[PDB]
């Protein structure tokens, strides 16, 4: 029962380990262990429940333990001290093979093999802690211990890839406990958390690890918005060291989401549009990605209303995520028709939903767009239209008030109109024949460059597998 | 905590306040640097002037920030 | 098979309260006898809410009579030697009864067995179609769709020309049933040319549908040839009321009567669009187009109009017309503005160079996004 | 199996899904102009007669 | 051209793997 | 005008008839729509082909 | 602000800082500063004297110059140290 289960689960762990162990120590095959590690987290999360969970303790004992016996003890203590011959020496399956850590030599300290093993062991504890949902004591105990250990290491390109993943867990775990309960102690430790990412990012730029650079930047941009600091976020993005060389599309998609938010509040809805479209493209469409797609659609719709444009009606409809976007359709109806009352009623009703994501705050500003949008439409239908007509239609308070709103608009040039005070009408200036002017050329010049950039992307990537095969023997 | 108190103190004209501020920033320069990147041209001006006597320290701060950002050339 | 549609169409008028109370109760007289006669309780249960237990004793009796009759008939004709064919015909006969009481569930079962057995190749095609007919009875669009594929699977293997004529009309009803009329107008007018009816909904229906769909899709010149100068539609004259209303609307548009045009729109809506179950959905959708069309032609012919000339021709007031016009203008099928101040309706109608430029660049953006999509994935892999 | 580490971690920061919170808490835009038309025609007609 | 070359690489991976296993079995 | 043998414009708001005998715009753009039309289907096909990698 | 961050003074002092930025005529910053505050004043103070810079912004964004002038003119009632901004805003 217990003995069988502990050991069998442990067997699989060592097979996975051997593969990653062998590959890092024979040249730098850097990319290949990384693909294994992705698959590893998934396989491990599913494992843990089946075949007991003190399978990890056996593993600790079995190999060399420099601090990890104490860590594993601490976890065991937390959920009640468990006993079944779980005293050290319980497991020992090294047996003098150099691939399973030569038993005499390692212990004497005539050879060291602990380095990379320790980083991996830690990876299993953070994963398992998070799995189980052991918070409070352990969360602080864990951060306290892992950060000085990496900073005592001088981490290879390979070892850089491993610790990019502990970093993820360090950030999330501090957040969940904070969200669970507010306390000043949570607040003191928050300052500690920012400072550690900033010190490490410089180290990781010098090793130029595409994995490591990517993970850290996504976390930091997120932290900053949560504390609302505009200023720090703009400086942090200026550098743009955020790679696109090899990193996953999931990593990028996060990166693009944050930029959209950031640019939107700074009043650039032009560039926010491009980012938010770009964030959807990179993201895979998966169920495991559903949370991201759901937040992405919502942000897209807010940007289109901030610009002054109505997004496609069909977006909200044809979605199978249509239920969440119930608040979005009511906002879209109110904006397009210029109904002053409707708009205010909508945001009262869906307020608490909207407050969750702090889209409430954007919607206070979307009050302005109700009016802006409606005037653009009235002007496109009716070229010369007395100021008197406009007010009657959309119940605007007076001729003096609407004149001024229109006046403001055409400074920023959205309406593309002009007021003729003396004659009492507002006259749209549009006339077409912009094909004759130089503007299509500017447009088309860019479109050529985009195709060329496609070709290059094709060419470079294409040759990288072929190298492998020519070098490999073939039948 | 934030750099906002720290910034505020540079501005105070009185000599002793500016000097104290330099020490304060220096502690947290390695810990936090992205927030005072904005305000680099001021730290630089203090280094230029030859009224300060912790003048050597003022340039040290500029240098430290610049290496963390990754503009290594500006640092050296 | 035949009555199942007859019932429901009557029942629809009873259901609606949009219909006049006089008409409602005409329908009530007619349907009530047939509920009892064809024993229609499973379907009737839905509608009764939705607008005797004897019907049921009858159901159950009928169920059992018809149910038992057919049962032991097959037990008889398993024995009597002809194992592929006579069991098949007897199994069909159970399904005939199921189809009679408007329970589609039980129909599918018995006709399933019929198919298993290997019989005349024509016969099978007839059965598949019968199942697709049941989709029109429930008027579930989703039911008709799935089934019509099985029919189309066997049609061309069968290479039946004869039941190939039926295919057209049924597929007419799917495309009619749906909003998309571009496929519907073509299909339904071809079936006026060739009609083959073996247990099929009247020929009258086909006339009504061609006329509507003709109007929506076709341009001016092709409307004349295919609808106005249809020989069948003219030869059948306007007999039935539904057919009559649409015919008056068609002539006026083409003869460029403007005064009676708007009253015929009101007429058509009262008497054509709303009685039909399939184009009840599309009543709103049809009208919006047709009001744009009278205008779209008129603006072609006129650089300027007054509001009073435009309004008055149709027989609507200036205030009403102006409002209707601002609804249609942002869809950009009219390409005109209304000068309030000068009181003229000026016509922009751009077919300039700049116009043709827009249409090709929107196609190019569609191709641009796809290239990025295939490439980026495949490069990572 | 390669993206899976990343997609699951990404999701965790949105927290839950929103999509299933929603039911617990709780002429694409145009309106059919036949109804409007009906009323209007009656109103025209009167004035027209007495013109 | 991007895809076709990839297709070729994909088959060849299998060709080379199979060499290694078969050399082991034979020996 | 609808038939189309003189295709011009009538002014209700005044009383002029303007005649335009201008036949038709660019073949160039038209045949360009056809080439783009083919290409949209073609890329999806290729992508179908390219799925042995997946 | 001490004891995690209440005091009646908190509402009054914020209102005067935000009004400064509208008088420097940087809306860009008005929004940037507002972002920071948002988490800490969601409904804690809600809008109090805080409403004075908030309405003003809203009306210039709409582009209601009329309505804006009206608020300032009526703003002479509440002059207490707020006139330090009121005068700038006229011009």
Image (cartoon, coloured by chain):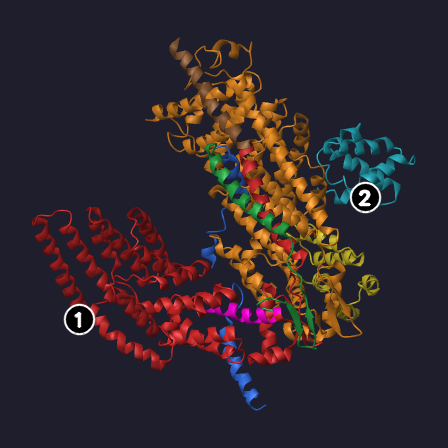
Chain colours: A orange, B cyan, C red, D blue, E brown, F green, G yellow
C118 horizontally vs G11: left or right: left
Front position in the image: G73 or C232: C232
- Name the secondary structure under disc 2: helix
Q: Main secondary structure of the magenta part?
A: helix
Q: Which label is found at residue C356?
A: none
Between the C-alphas of marks 2 and 1, the distance is: 96 Å
Q: Residue furthest right?
A: B51
Of all chains, the one bearing label 1 is C
| Horizontal arrangement in the rendering, residue C136 relative to residue A335 (left or right) | left
> Residue C274: horizontal and vertical position, in percent?
41, 72
**Do the residues marked 2 and 1 share a common chain?**
no
Tell me the quarter of the image containing the C terminus of chain G.
bottom right
Where residue B9 is drawn, which disc sits there?
Answer: 2
Residue F42 in sight from this viewpoint? yes
Q: Is residue A185 visible?
A: no
Local packing at callout 2 (Cα closer than 10 Å; few below 14, some 14-19, many 20+) is some
Q: Position of residue A139 (x, y in %)?
A: 54, 36
Q: Position of residue A256 (x, y in %)?
A: 62, 43
Q: Is residue C186 magenta?
A: no
Q: Which element type, helix, strand or loop, lies under badge 1?
A: helix
Task: Look at the picture and state if C155 lies above or below C259.
Answer: above
Measuring from the top left, give residue B22's x and y in whole percent.
81, 37
Judge depth for marks 2 and 1 and give the one in front. 1
Q: Is residue C290 magenta?
A: yes
Chain label for disc 2: B
Residue C315 image-quadrant placement: bottom right
Magenta highlight range: C282-300
The residue at the far front in this view is F5
Residue under pointer 1: C54
Q: Is residue G6 above or below residue A368?
A: above
Give the residue at x 49% y 79%: C263
């Amino acid at each position: 029962l217990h003995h069988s289960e502990k050991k069998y689960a442990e067997e699989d762990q060592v097979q996975e380990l051997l593969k990653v162990l062998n590959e890092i120590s024979k040249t730098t095959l850097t990319l290949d262990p990384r693909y294994i590690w992705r698959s590893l987290k998934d396989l491990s999360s599913l494992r843990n429940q089946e075949l007991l969970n003190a399978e990890t303790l056996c593993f600790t004992v079995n190999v060399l333990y420099p601090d990890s016996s104490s860590f594993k003890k601490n976890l065991l203590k937390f959920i009640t001290s468990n006993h079944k011959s779980s005293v050290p020496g319980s497991a020992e399956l090294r047996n003098s093979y150099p691939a399973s850590f030569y038993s005499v030599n390692t212990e004497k300290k005539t050879i060291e093999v602990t380095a990379e093993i320790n980083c991996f062991m830690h990876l299993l504890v953070q994963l398992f802690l998070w799995d189980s949902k052991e918070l409070e004591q352990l969360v602080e105990f864990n951060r306290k211990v892992v950060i000085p250990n990496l900073l005592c290491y001088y981490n290879l390109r390979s070892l850089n890839l491993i610790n990019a993943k502990l970093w993820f867990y360090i950030y999330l775990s501090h957040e969940t406990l904070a969200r669970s309960s507010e306390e000043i102690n949570s607040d003191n430790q928050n300052i500690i958390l920012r400072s550690t990412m900033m010190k490490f990012l410089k180290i990781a730029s010098l090793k130029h690890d595409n994995e490591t650079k990517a993970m850290l930047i996504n976390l930091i941009l997120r932290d900053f918005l949560n504390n609302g600091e505009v200023d720090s976020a703009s400086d942090f993005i200026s550098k743009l060291e955020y790679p696109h060389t090899d990193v996953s599309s999931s990593l990028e998609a996060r990166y693009f989401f944050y930029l959209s938010k950031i640019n939107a509040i700074q009043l650039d809805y032009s560039t926010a549009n491009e980012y938010i479209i770009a964030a959807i493209r990179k993201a895979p469409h998966n169920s495991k990605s559903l949370g991201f797609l759901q937040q992405s659609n919502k942000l897209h719709c807010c940007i289109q209303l901030l610009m002054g444009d109505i997004p496609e009606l069909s977006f909200f409809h044809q979605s199978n995520m249509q239920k969440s976007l119930l608040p979005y359709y009511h906002l879209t109806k109110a904006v397009k028709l210029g109904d002053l009352k409707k708009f205010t009623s909508t945001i009262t009703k869906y307020k608490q939903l909207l407050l969750k994501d702090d889209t409430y705050q954007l919607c206070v500003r979307l009050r302005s767009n109700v009016i802006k949008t409606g005037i653009r439409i009235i002007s496109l239908t009716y070229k010369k239209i007395s100021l008197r007509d406009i007010c009657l239609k959309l119940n605007l308070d007076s001729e003096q008030t609407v004149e001024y709103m229109v006046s403001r608009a055409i400074r920023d040039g959205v309406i593309e109109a002009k007021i003729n005070h003396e004659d009492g009408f507002i006259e749209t200036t549009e006339l077409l024949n912009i094909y004759d002017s130089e503007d299509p050329q500017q447009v088309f010049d860019e479109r050529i460059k985009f195709a060329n950039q496609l070709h290059d992307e094709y060419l470079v990537s294409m040759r990288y597998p072929e190298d492998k095969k020519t070098q490999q023997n073939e039948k | 905590t934030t750099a906002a108190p720290l910034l505020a103190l540079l501005r105070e004209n009185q000599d002793s306040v500016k000097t104290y501020a330099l020490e304060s920033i220096n502690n947290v320069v390695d810990q936090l640097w992205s927030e005072i990147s904005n305000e680099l041209p001021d730290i630089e001006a203090l280094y230029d002037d030859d009224t300060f006597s912790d003048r050597e320290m003022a340039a040290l701060i500029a240098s430290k920030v610049y290496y963390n950002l990754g503009e290594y050339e500006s640092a050296v | 098979r035949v009555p199942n549609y007859e019932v429901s169409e009557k029942a629809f008028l009873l259901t609606q309260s949009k219909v006049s109370i006089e008409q409602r109760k005409e329908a009530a007289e007619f349907v009530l006898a047939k509920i009892k006669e064809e024993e229609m309780a499973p379907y009737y249960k839905y509608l009764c809410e939705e607008y005797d237990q004897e019907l049921y004793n009858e159901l159950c009796k009928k169920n059992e009579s018809k149910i038992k009759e057919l049962n032991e008939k097959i037990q008889k004709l398993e024995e009597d030697d002809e194992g592929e064919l006579e069991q098949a015909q007897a199994w069909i006969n159970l399904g005939e009864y199921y189809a009679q009481i408007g329970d589609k569930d039980n129909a599918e079962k018995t006709l399933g067995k019929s198919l298993s057995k290997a019989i005349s190749t024509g016969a099978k095609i007839d059965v598949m179609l019968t199942i697709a007919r049941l989709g029109f009875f429930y008027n579930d669009q989703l039911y008709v769709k799935e089934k019509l594929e099985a029919v189309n699977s066997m049609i061309e293997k069968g290479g039946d020309w004869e039941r190939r004529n039926r295919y057209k009309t049924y597929y007419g009803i799917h495309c009619l049933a749906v909003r998309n009329f571009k496929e519907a107008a073509k299909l339904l007018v071809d079936s006026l040319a060739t009609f083959t009816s073996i247990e099929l909904t009247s020929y009258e229906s086909i006339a009504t549908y061609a006329s509507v769909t003709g109007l929506f899709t076709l341009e001016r010149t092709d409307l004349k040839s295919k609808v106005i100068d249809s020989p069948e539609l003219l030869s059948l004259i306007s007999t039935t009321a539904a057919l009559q209303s649409i015919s008056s609307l068609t002539i006026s548009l083409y003869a460029s009567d403007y005064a009676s045009y708007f009253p015929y729109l009101l007429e058509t809506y009262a008497n054509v669009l709303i009685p039909c179950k399939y184009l009840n959905r599309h009543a709103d959708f049809f009208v919006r187009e047709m009001r744009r069309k009278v205008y779209a032609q008129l603006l072609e012919s006129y650089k300027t109009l007054s509001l009073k000339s435009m309004a008055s021709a149709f027989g609507v007031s200036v205030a009403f017309l102006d409002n209707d016009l601002g609804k249609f203008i942002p869809n950009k099928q009219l390409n005109c503005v209304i000068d309030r101040v000068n009181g003229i309706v000026e016509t922009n109608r751009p077919d300039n160079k700049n116009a043709q430029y827009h249409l090709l660049v929107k196609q190019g953006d569609g191709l641009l996004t796809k290239l990025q999509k295939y490439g980026a994935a495949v490069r990572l892999t | 199996t390669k993206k899976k580490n990343e997609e699951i971690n990404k999701k965790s920061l949105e927290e839950d899904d929103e999509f299933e919170d929603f039911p617990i808490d709780t002429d694409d835009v145009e309106v059919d102009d036949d109804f409007t038309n009906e009323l209007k025609a009656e109103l025209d007609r009167y004035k027209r007669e007495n013109q | 051209e991007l895809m076709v070359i990839y297709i070729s690489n994909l088959v060849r991976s299998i060709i080379a793997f199979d060499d290694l296993i078969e050399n082991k079995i034979q020996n | 005008i609808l038939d189309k043998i003189f295709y011009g414009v009538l002014d209700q708001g005044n009383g002029w008839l303007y005649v335009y005998e201008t036949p038709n715009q660019d073949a160039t753009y038209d045949s360009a729509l056809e080439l783009v039309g083919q290409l949209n289907k073609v890329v999806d096909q290729l992508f179908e082909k390219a799925s042995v990698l997946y | 602000n001490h004891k995690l961050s209440e005091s009646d003074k908190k509402s009054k002092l914020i209102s005067l800082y935000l009004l400064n930025l509208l008088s420097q005529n940087n809306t860009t910053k008005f929004h940037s500063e507002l972002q920071y505050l948002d988490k800490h004043i969601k409904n804690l103070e809600d809008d109090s004297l805080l409403s004075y810079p908030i309405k003003l912004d809203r009306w210039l964004m709409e582009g209601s110059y009329q309505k804006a002038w009206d608020l300032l003119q009526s703003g002479s009632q509440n002059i207490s140290e707020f006139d330090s901004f009121t005068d700038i805003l006229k011009s």
